[PDB]
C-alpha cells in the first residue's frame, strides 16, 4: 500500500510493504490505519512511523477479511470485531462471531457497530437488530450518512444492488444489474454511482470489467 | 477547476526490460499459488495464437494479473 | 480395561502408585513430545506408538467410569440416608461400572449435580496435581490431523470420554480455559483455551464424518453450562458462562441445532445441542443476544413440527421438543407451563392480556340480570330489583 | 385455504388445517345448560354485593338449596 500525492506532484510520499487494506482517519485526517491479517497498525502522515499497533492474542476473532476502521469521533477501532479505546491502548469488548468473513464497520451516527448482519450498540453492547438482507455485502454510506448501499460479495458477485435506510434499516430497493458487481463508490454530492461491472459470463480467463455511471433518482 | 497532477511517478522506460523484470515475477507468484499444469498450458495456448510477438508477452501479464487479482478476491487464501 | 469392574482391583490400584505409573505412560510418548516428534520417523515406532496412546485412553476411560459409580455410592448413601435408599453393604466384589455410556454413564454425570458442591476426589486431586488435562488437551490437538487411519477416530473418542467424566469437579472446569499450551495445524506452537478445541470438535471442522465424537464433545460443554442454581459457586458457573460465550460458543450451538447430515443420530445431536443453550441462556448477556437472532425470528417452531426421523418420534424427537419449550420460556415473558400461542409475537400479547386489570361497574350487570329475569318468566323479583337499584327501562 | 376446507366466512383465526377443523365443530356445536346453573349464580352474586332483598324474593321463583 502506498500513500501517494495528488496536489501537483505524484510520488510515494510514504511506503508500506505490509498491510492489505489501508484507511484514513475520518474527522481529523492526520492518521492512516492499515491491517495485515489480524494485526492493525496506526500510522502518522507527517513522519510515517508506527504510532500504536493494537492486537490482543487472547481476544481476536480471526476474520477472513479484517479491515480496521475508525469511528467518526476518531476514538474507536474495529480490529477483529474488538473495539479499541485509542486513548490508552486497551481493548473494550469482543463481539460474537457469526459469519466467518467480515470484521464490521461503524454506522455514521456514532451510536452503533455494524457487524455483517448483526447491529450492535456502542455503550450498552446489546444486539439491537438483525437484518438478513445484509448477508455478506460490503456497505457504503452517503456522505450525510442517510442511506446505506449494498453490493453482494458471494462464483458470481453482485447480481443486483441493495439500497438501505440508515435509521431503521428498511430496504428501499434492489435494482437488478444483470452483470456482476465488483466495486461500488458514490459521490459526496449524491449524484452518481461508480459501478465496476464485468461483461461476459463468469469467466476467470476473460474479464471485461467496465465502469458504468448511474444517476441517482431518475427513472 | 481541478488540476490533474504531474506524472512524476515511477516511470517504466525500458518496457522491453521492465517486462522482463516482472514477467518472471508474474511466474514467481503463480507457482506459489497454483500448479504448473494450467501455467504451461495457457502459456502454450497463447504461444500457439500470439507467438513471440509481444502480443502474448503483455497478454500473459494481462491474464495472470487478471486471475491473481480475482483469485485473491473470490476468497481462496492461496488459490 | 476389564478388571476395573472388580472393586478389590481398584482398591489395590491406589494403594500403589497407580496413575503416577499410568499417566507417566502418556507423558513419555513421542508422538506427543512436540520437541521430539521430528526425530524418529520409521513405521515401527509410530504405528505402535499411535496404538499405545489408543489403549491408555481406554484404560483411563474404564478407570473413571468405575470411580464415577464408586463416589455416587458415597453420595446416594451419605446424603440421602434412608430418604430413598437402603443401607445394606457387606462389601462384595461386584461388577458395578453400569456398562452403558449411551444411557447410564451419561445419567450418572447428571445426577452428581446434586452433589456436595465442594467435591473432593482422590481420582481428581491426583489428576490435577499432575495437571494432565492439558496433556489430554494436547492429545486432542495432535490427533486432529493424522489423516492416515491409525484408529485416530477412537483415540480422540476415548480421549473426550476421559474429559467428560472429569468435568463434574468444579476446579477442573476452571482449568478448561487457563492452561493453554497447545499446537495446531500450522506446524507451529500456538496458545489457545481448551474450550475452543472442544467447540471445534463439536462443529465438524475436524473429524468430518464422525458422530459419537460430536456427542462426546457436547457432553463436555453441558457439564460446564447447565449446572446448579447455586456468590462463589454461582460465580464459578458465571465464569464458565463468560468463557464459553467468549470463545464463539453461540455460533456453534446454533449450527448444531439444525444438523441434518448424520440422519441416524440427527435427533440426538440436536437435543444435546439445545440442552446446552437452556443452560447457557441463564447468562444475562446471552439472554439478549439469542433473543434477536433468526432462531427467535422464526424456524424454532419449524424444528419442532417437521418430525424428521419418525423412528425416534415417540423416543427422541419428543424430548427435543421438551428441551426446546424450556428455551422459549426462558428468553421471553415467562409462561407458567401453559401450551398456548407459542409464537414470539403472540407471546407478548398473552403477557399483557393476562396481567390486565379488567374492571366494570355494577350497573352493566344488574341491567343484564333484570333483562334476563323478565325474559325467562321469573318476574316477581324484577320489580323487587327496582328497590335495590335504579331501573332505566320498565 | 378457504375453498378446500370447511368454509371460514372471512374470519382470520387459526389458519392451520388441523386447527381449522376444530373451529368448524366448536362454532357449530349446540351448547345448552339448565336454568338452575345460572340462577344459583345470580343469587350468589346478589347476596355477595350487598343487594340482598331480592334473594329471599328469588326463593319465591325457584328452589334455593343454599341459605
Image (cartoon, grey):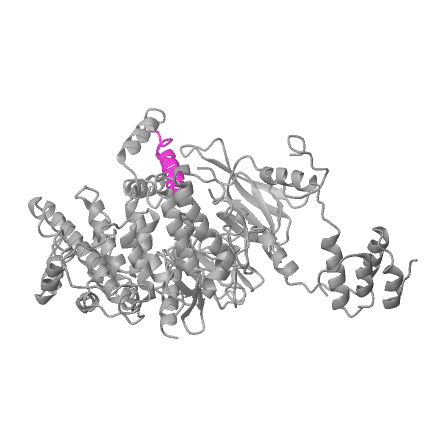
What is the chief secondary structure element of the magenta stretch?
A: helix
Number of marks present in the image shown? 0
User: Residue C253's x, y, as percent?
Assistant: 40, 52
Q: Which quadrant: the N terminus of chain A?
A: bottom left
Q: Examine the rendering and report whether any part of residue A51 can be seen.
A: no
- Camera sees residue C96: yes
**Left or right relative to C190: residue C272:** right
Residue visible at 24% across and 54% down in the picture: C161
Which of A42 and C208 lies nearest the eye of the viewer? C208
Residue C114 among those drawn in magenta:
no
Query: Quick check: C181 above or below A200?
Result: below
Residue C168 location in percent, x, y?
29, 63
- Give percent across and percent down for residue B72: 38, 44
Q: Nearer the viewer, residue C91 or B30?
A: C91
- Find the magenta span and give its range: B53-72
Please name the residue shown 44% across and 37% down the image. Answer: A155
Amino acid at each position: 500500500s502506498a500513500l501517494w500525492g495528488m496536489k501537483s506532484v505524484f510520488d510515494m510520499k510514504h511506503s508500506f510493504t505490509e498491510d492489505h487494506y489501508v484507511e484514513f482517519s475520518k474527522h481529523s485526517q492526520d492518521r492512516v490505519i492499515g491491517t495485515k491479517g489480524d494485526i492493525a497498525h496506526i500510522y502518522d502522515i507527517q513522519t510515517g512511523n508506527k504510532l500504536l499497533t493494537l492486537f490482543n492474542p487472547d481476544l481476536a476473532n480471526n476474520y477472513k477479511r479484517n479491515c480496521a476502521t475508525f469511528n467518526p469521533t476518531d476514538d474507536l477501532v474495529l480490529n477483529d470485531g474488538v473495539l479499541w479505546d485509542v486513548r490508552s491502548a486497551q481493548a473494550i469488548h469482543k463481539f460474537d462471531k457469526f459469519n466467518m468473513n467480515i470484521s464490521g464497520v461503524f454506522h455514521p451516527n456514532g451510536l452503533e457497530v455494524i457487524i455483517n448482519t448483526e447491529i450492535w450498540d456502542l455503550r450498552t453492547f446489546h444486539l439491537l437488530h438483525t437484518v438478513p438482507a445484509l448477508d455478506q455485502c460490503r456497505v457504503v454510506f452517503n456522505h450525510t450518512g442517510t442511506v446505506m448501499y449494498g453490493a453482494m460479495l458471494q462464483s458470481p458477485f453482485g447480481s443486483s444492488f441493495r439500497t438501505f435506510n440508515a435509521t431503521d434499516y428498511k430496504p428501499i430497493a434492489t435494482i437488478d444489474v444483470k452483470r456482476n458487481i465488483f466495486d461500488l463508490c458514490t459521490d459526496t454530492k449524491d449524484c452518481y454511482l461508480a459501478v465496476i461491472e464485468n461483461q461476459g459470463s463468469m469467466d476467470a480467463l476473460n474479464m471485461d470489467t467496465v465502469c458504468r455511471l448511474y444517476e441517482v433518482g431518475r427513472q | 477547476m481541478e488540476q490533474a497532477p504531474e506524472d512524476q511517478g515511477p516511470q517504466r522506460e525500458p518496457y522491453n526490460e521492465w517486462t522482463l523484470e516482472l514477467l518472471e515475477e508474474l511466474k514467481s507468484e503463480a507457482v506459489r499459488h497454483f500448479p504448473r499444469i494450467w501455467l504451461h498450458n495457457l502459456g502454450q495456448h497463447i504461444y500457439e495464437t500470439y507467438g513471440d510477438t509481444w502480443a502474448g508477452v503483455e497478454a500473459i501479464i494481462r491474464i495472470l494479473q487478471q486471475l491473481l487479482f480475482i483469485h485473491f478476491r473470490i476468497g481462496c487464501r492461496h488459490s | 480395561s476389564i478388571c476395573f469392574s472388580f472393586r478389590a482391583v481398584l482398591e489395590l490400584f491406589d494403594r500403589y502408585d497407580g496413575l503416577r505409573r499410568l499417566v507417566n505412560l502418556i507423558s513419555t510418548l513421542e508422538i506427543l513430545n512436540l520437541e521430539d516428534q521430528g526425530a524418529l520417523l520409521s513405521d515401527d515406532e509410530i504405528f505402535a506408538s499411535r496404538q499405545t496412546g489408543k489403549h491408555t485412553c481406554m484404560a483411563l476411560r474404564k478407570y473413571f467410569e468405575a470411580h464415577l459409580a464408586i463416589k455416587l455410592e458415597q453420595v446416594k448413601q451419605s446424603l440421602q440416608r434412608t430418604e430413598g435408599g437402603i443401607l445394606v453393604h457387606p462389601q462384595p466384589p461386584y461388577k458395578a461400572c453400569s456398562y452403558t455410556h449411551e444411557q447410564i454413564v451419561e445419567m450418572m454425570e447428571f445426577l452428581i449435580e446434586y452433589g456436595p458442591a465442594q467435591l473432593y476426589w482422590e481420582p481428581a486431586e491426583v489428576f490435577l496435581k499432575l495437571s494432565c488435562v492439558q496433556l489430554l488437551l494436547q492429545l486432542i490437538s495432535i490427533a486432529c490431523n493424522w489423516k492416515t487411519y491409525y484408529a485416530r477416530n477412537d483415540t480422540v473418542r476415548f480421549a473426550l470420554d476421559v474429559l467428560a467424566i472429569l468435568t463434574v469437579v468444579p476446579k477442573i472446569q476452571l482449568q478448561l480455559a487457563e492452561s493453554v499450551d497447545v499446537l495446531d495445524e500450522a506446524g507451529s506452537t500456538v496458545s489457545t483455551v481448551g474450550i475452543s478445541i472442544i467447540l471445534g470438535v463439536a462443529e465438524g471442522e475436524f473429524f468430518i464424518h464422525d458422530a459419537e465424537i460430536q456427542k462426546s464433545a457436547l457432553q463436555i460443554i453441558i457439564n460446564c453450562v447447565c449446572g446448579p442454581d447455586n456468590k462463589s459457586s454461582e460465580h464459578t458457573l458465571a465464569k464458565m458462562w463468560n468463557v464459553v460465550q467468549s470463545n464463539n460458543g453461540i455460533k456453534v450451538l446454533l449450527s448444531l441445532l439444525s444438523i441434518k447430515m448424520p440422519i441416524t443420530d440427527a435427533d440426538q445431536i440436536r437435543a444435546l445441542a439445545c440442552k446446552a443453550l437452556v443452560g447457557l441462556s441463564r447468562s444475562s448477556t446471552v439472554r439478549q443476544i439469542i433473543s434477536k437472532l433468526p432462531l427467535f425470528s422464526s424456524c424454532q417452531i419449524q424444528q419442532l413440527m417437521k418430525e424428521p426421523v419418525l423412528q425416534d418420534k415417540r423416543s427422541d424427537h419428543v424430548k427435543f421438543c421438551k428441551y426446546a419449550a424450556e428455551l422459549i420460556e426462558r428468553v421471553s415473558g415467562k409462561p407458567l407451563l401453559i401450551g398456548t400461542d407459542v409464537s414470539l409475537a403472540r407471546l407478548q400479547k398473552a403477557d399483557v392480556v393476562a396481567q390486565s386489570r379488567i374492571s366494570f361497574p355494577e350497573k352493566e350487570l344488574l341491567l343484564l340480570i333484570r333483562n334476563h329475569l323478565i325474559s325467562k318468566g321469573l318476574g316477581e323479583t324484577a320489580t323487587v330489583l327496582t328497590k335495590e337499584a335504579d331501573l332505566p327501562m320498565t
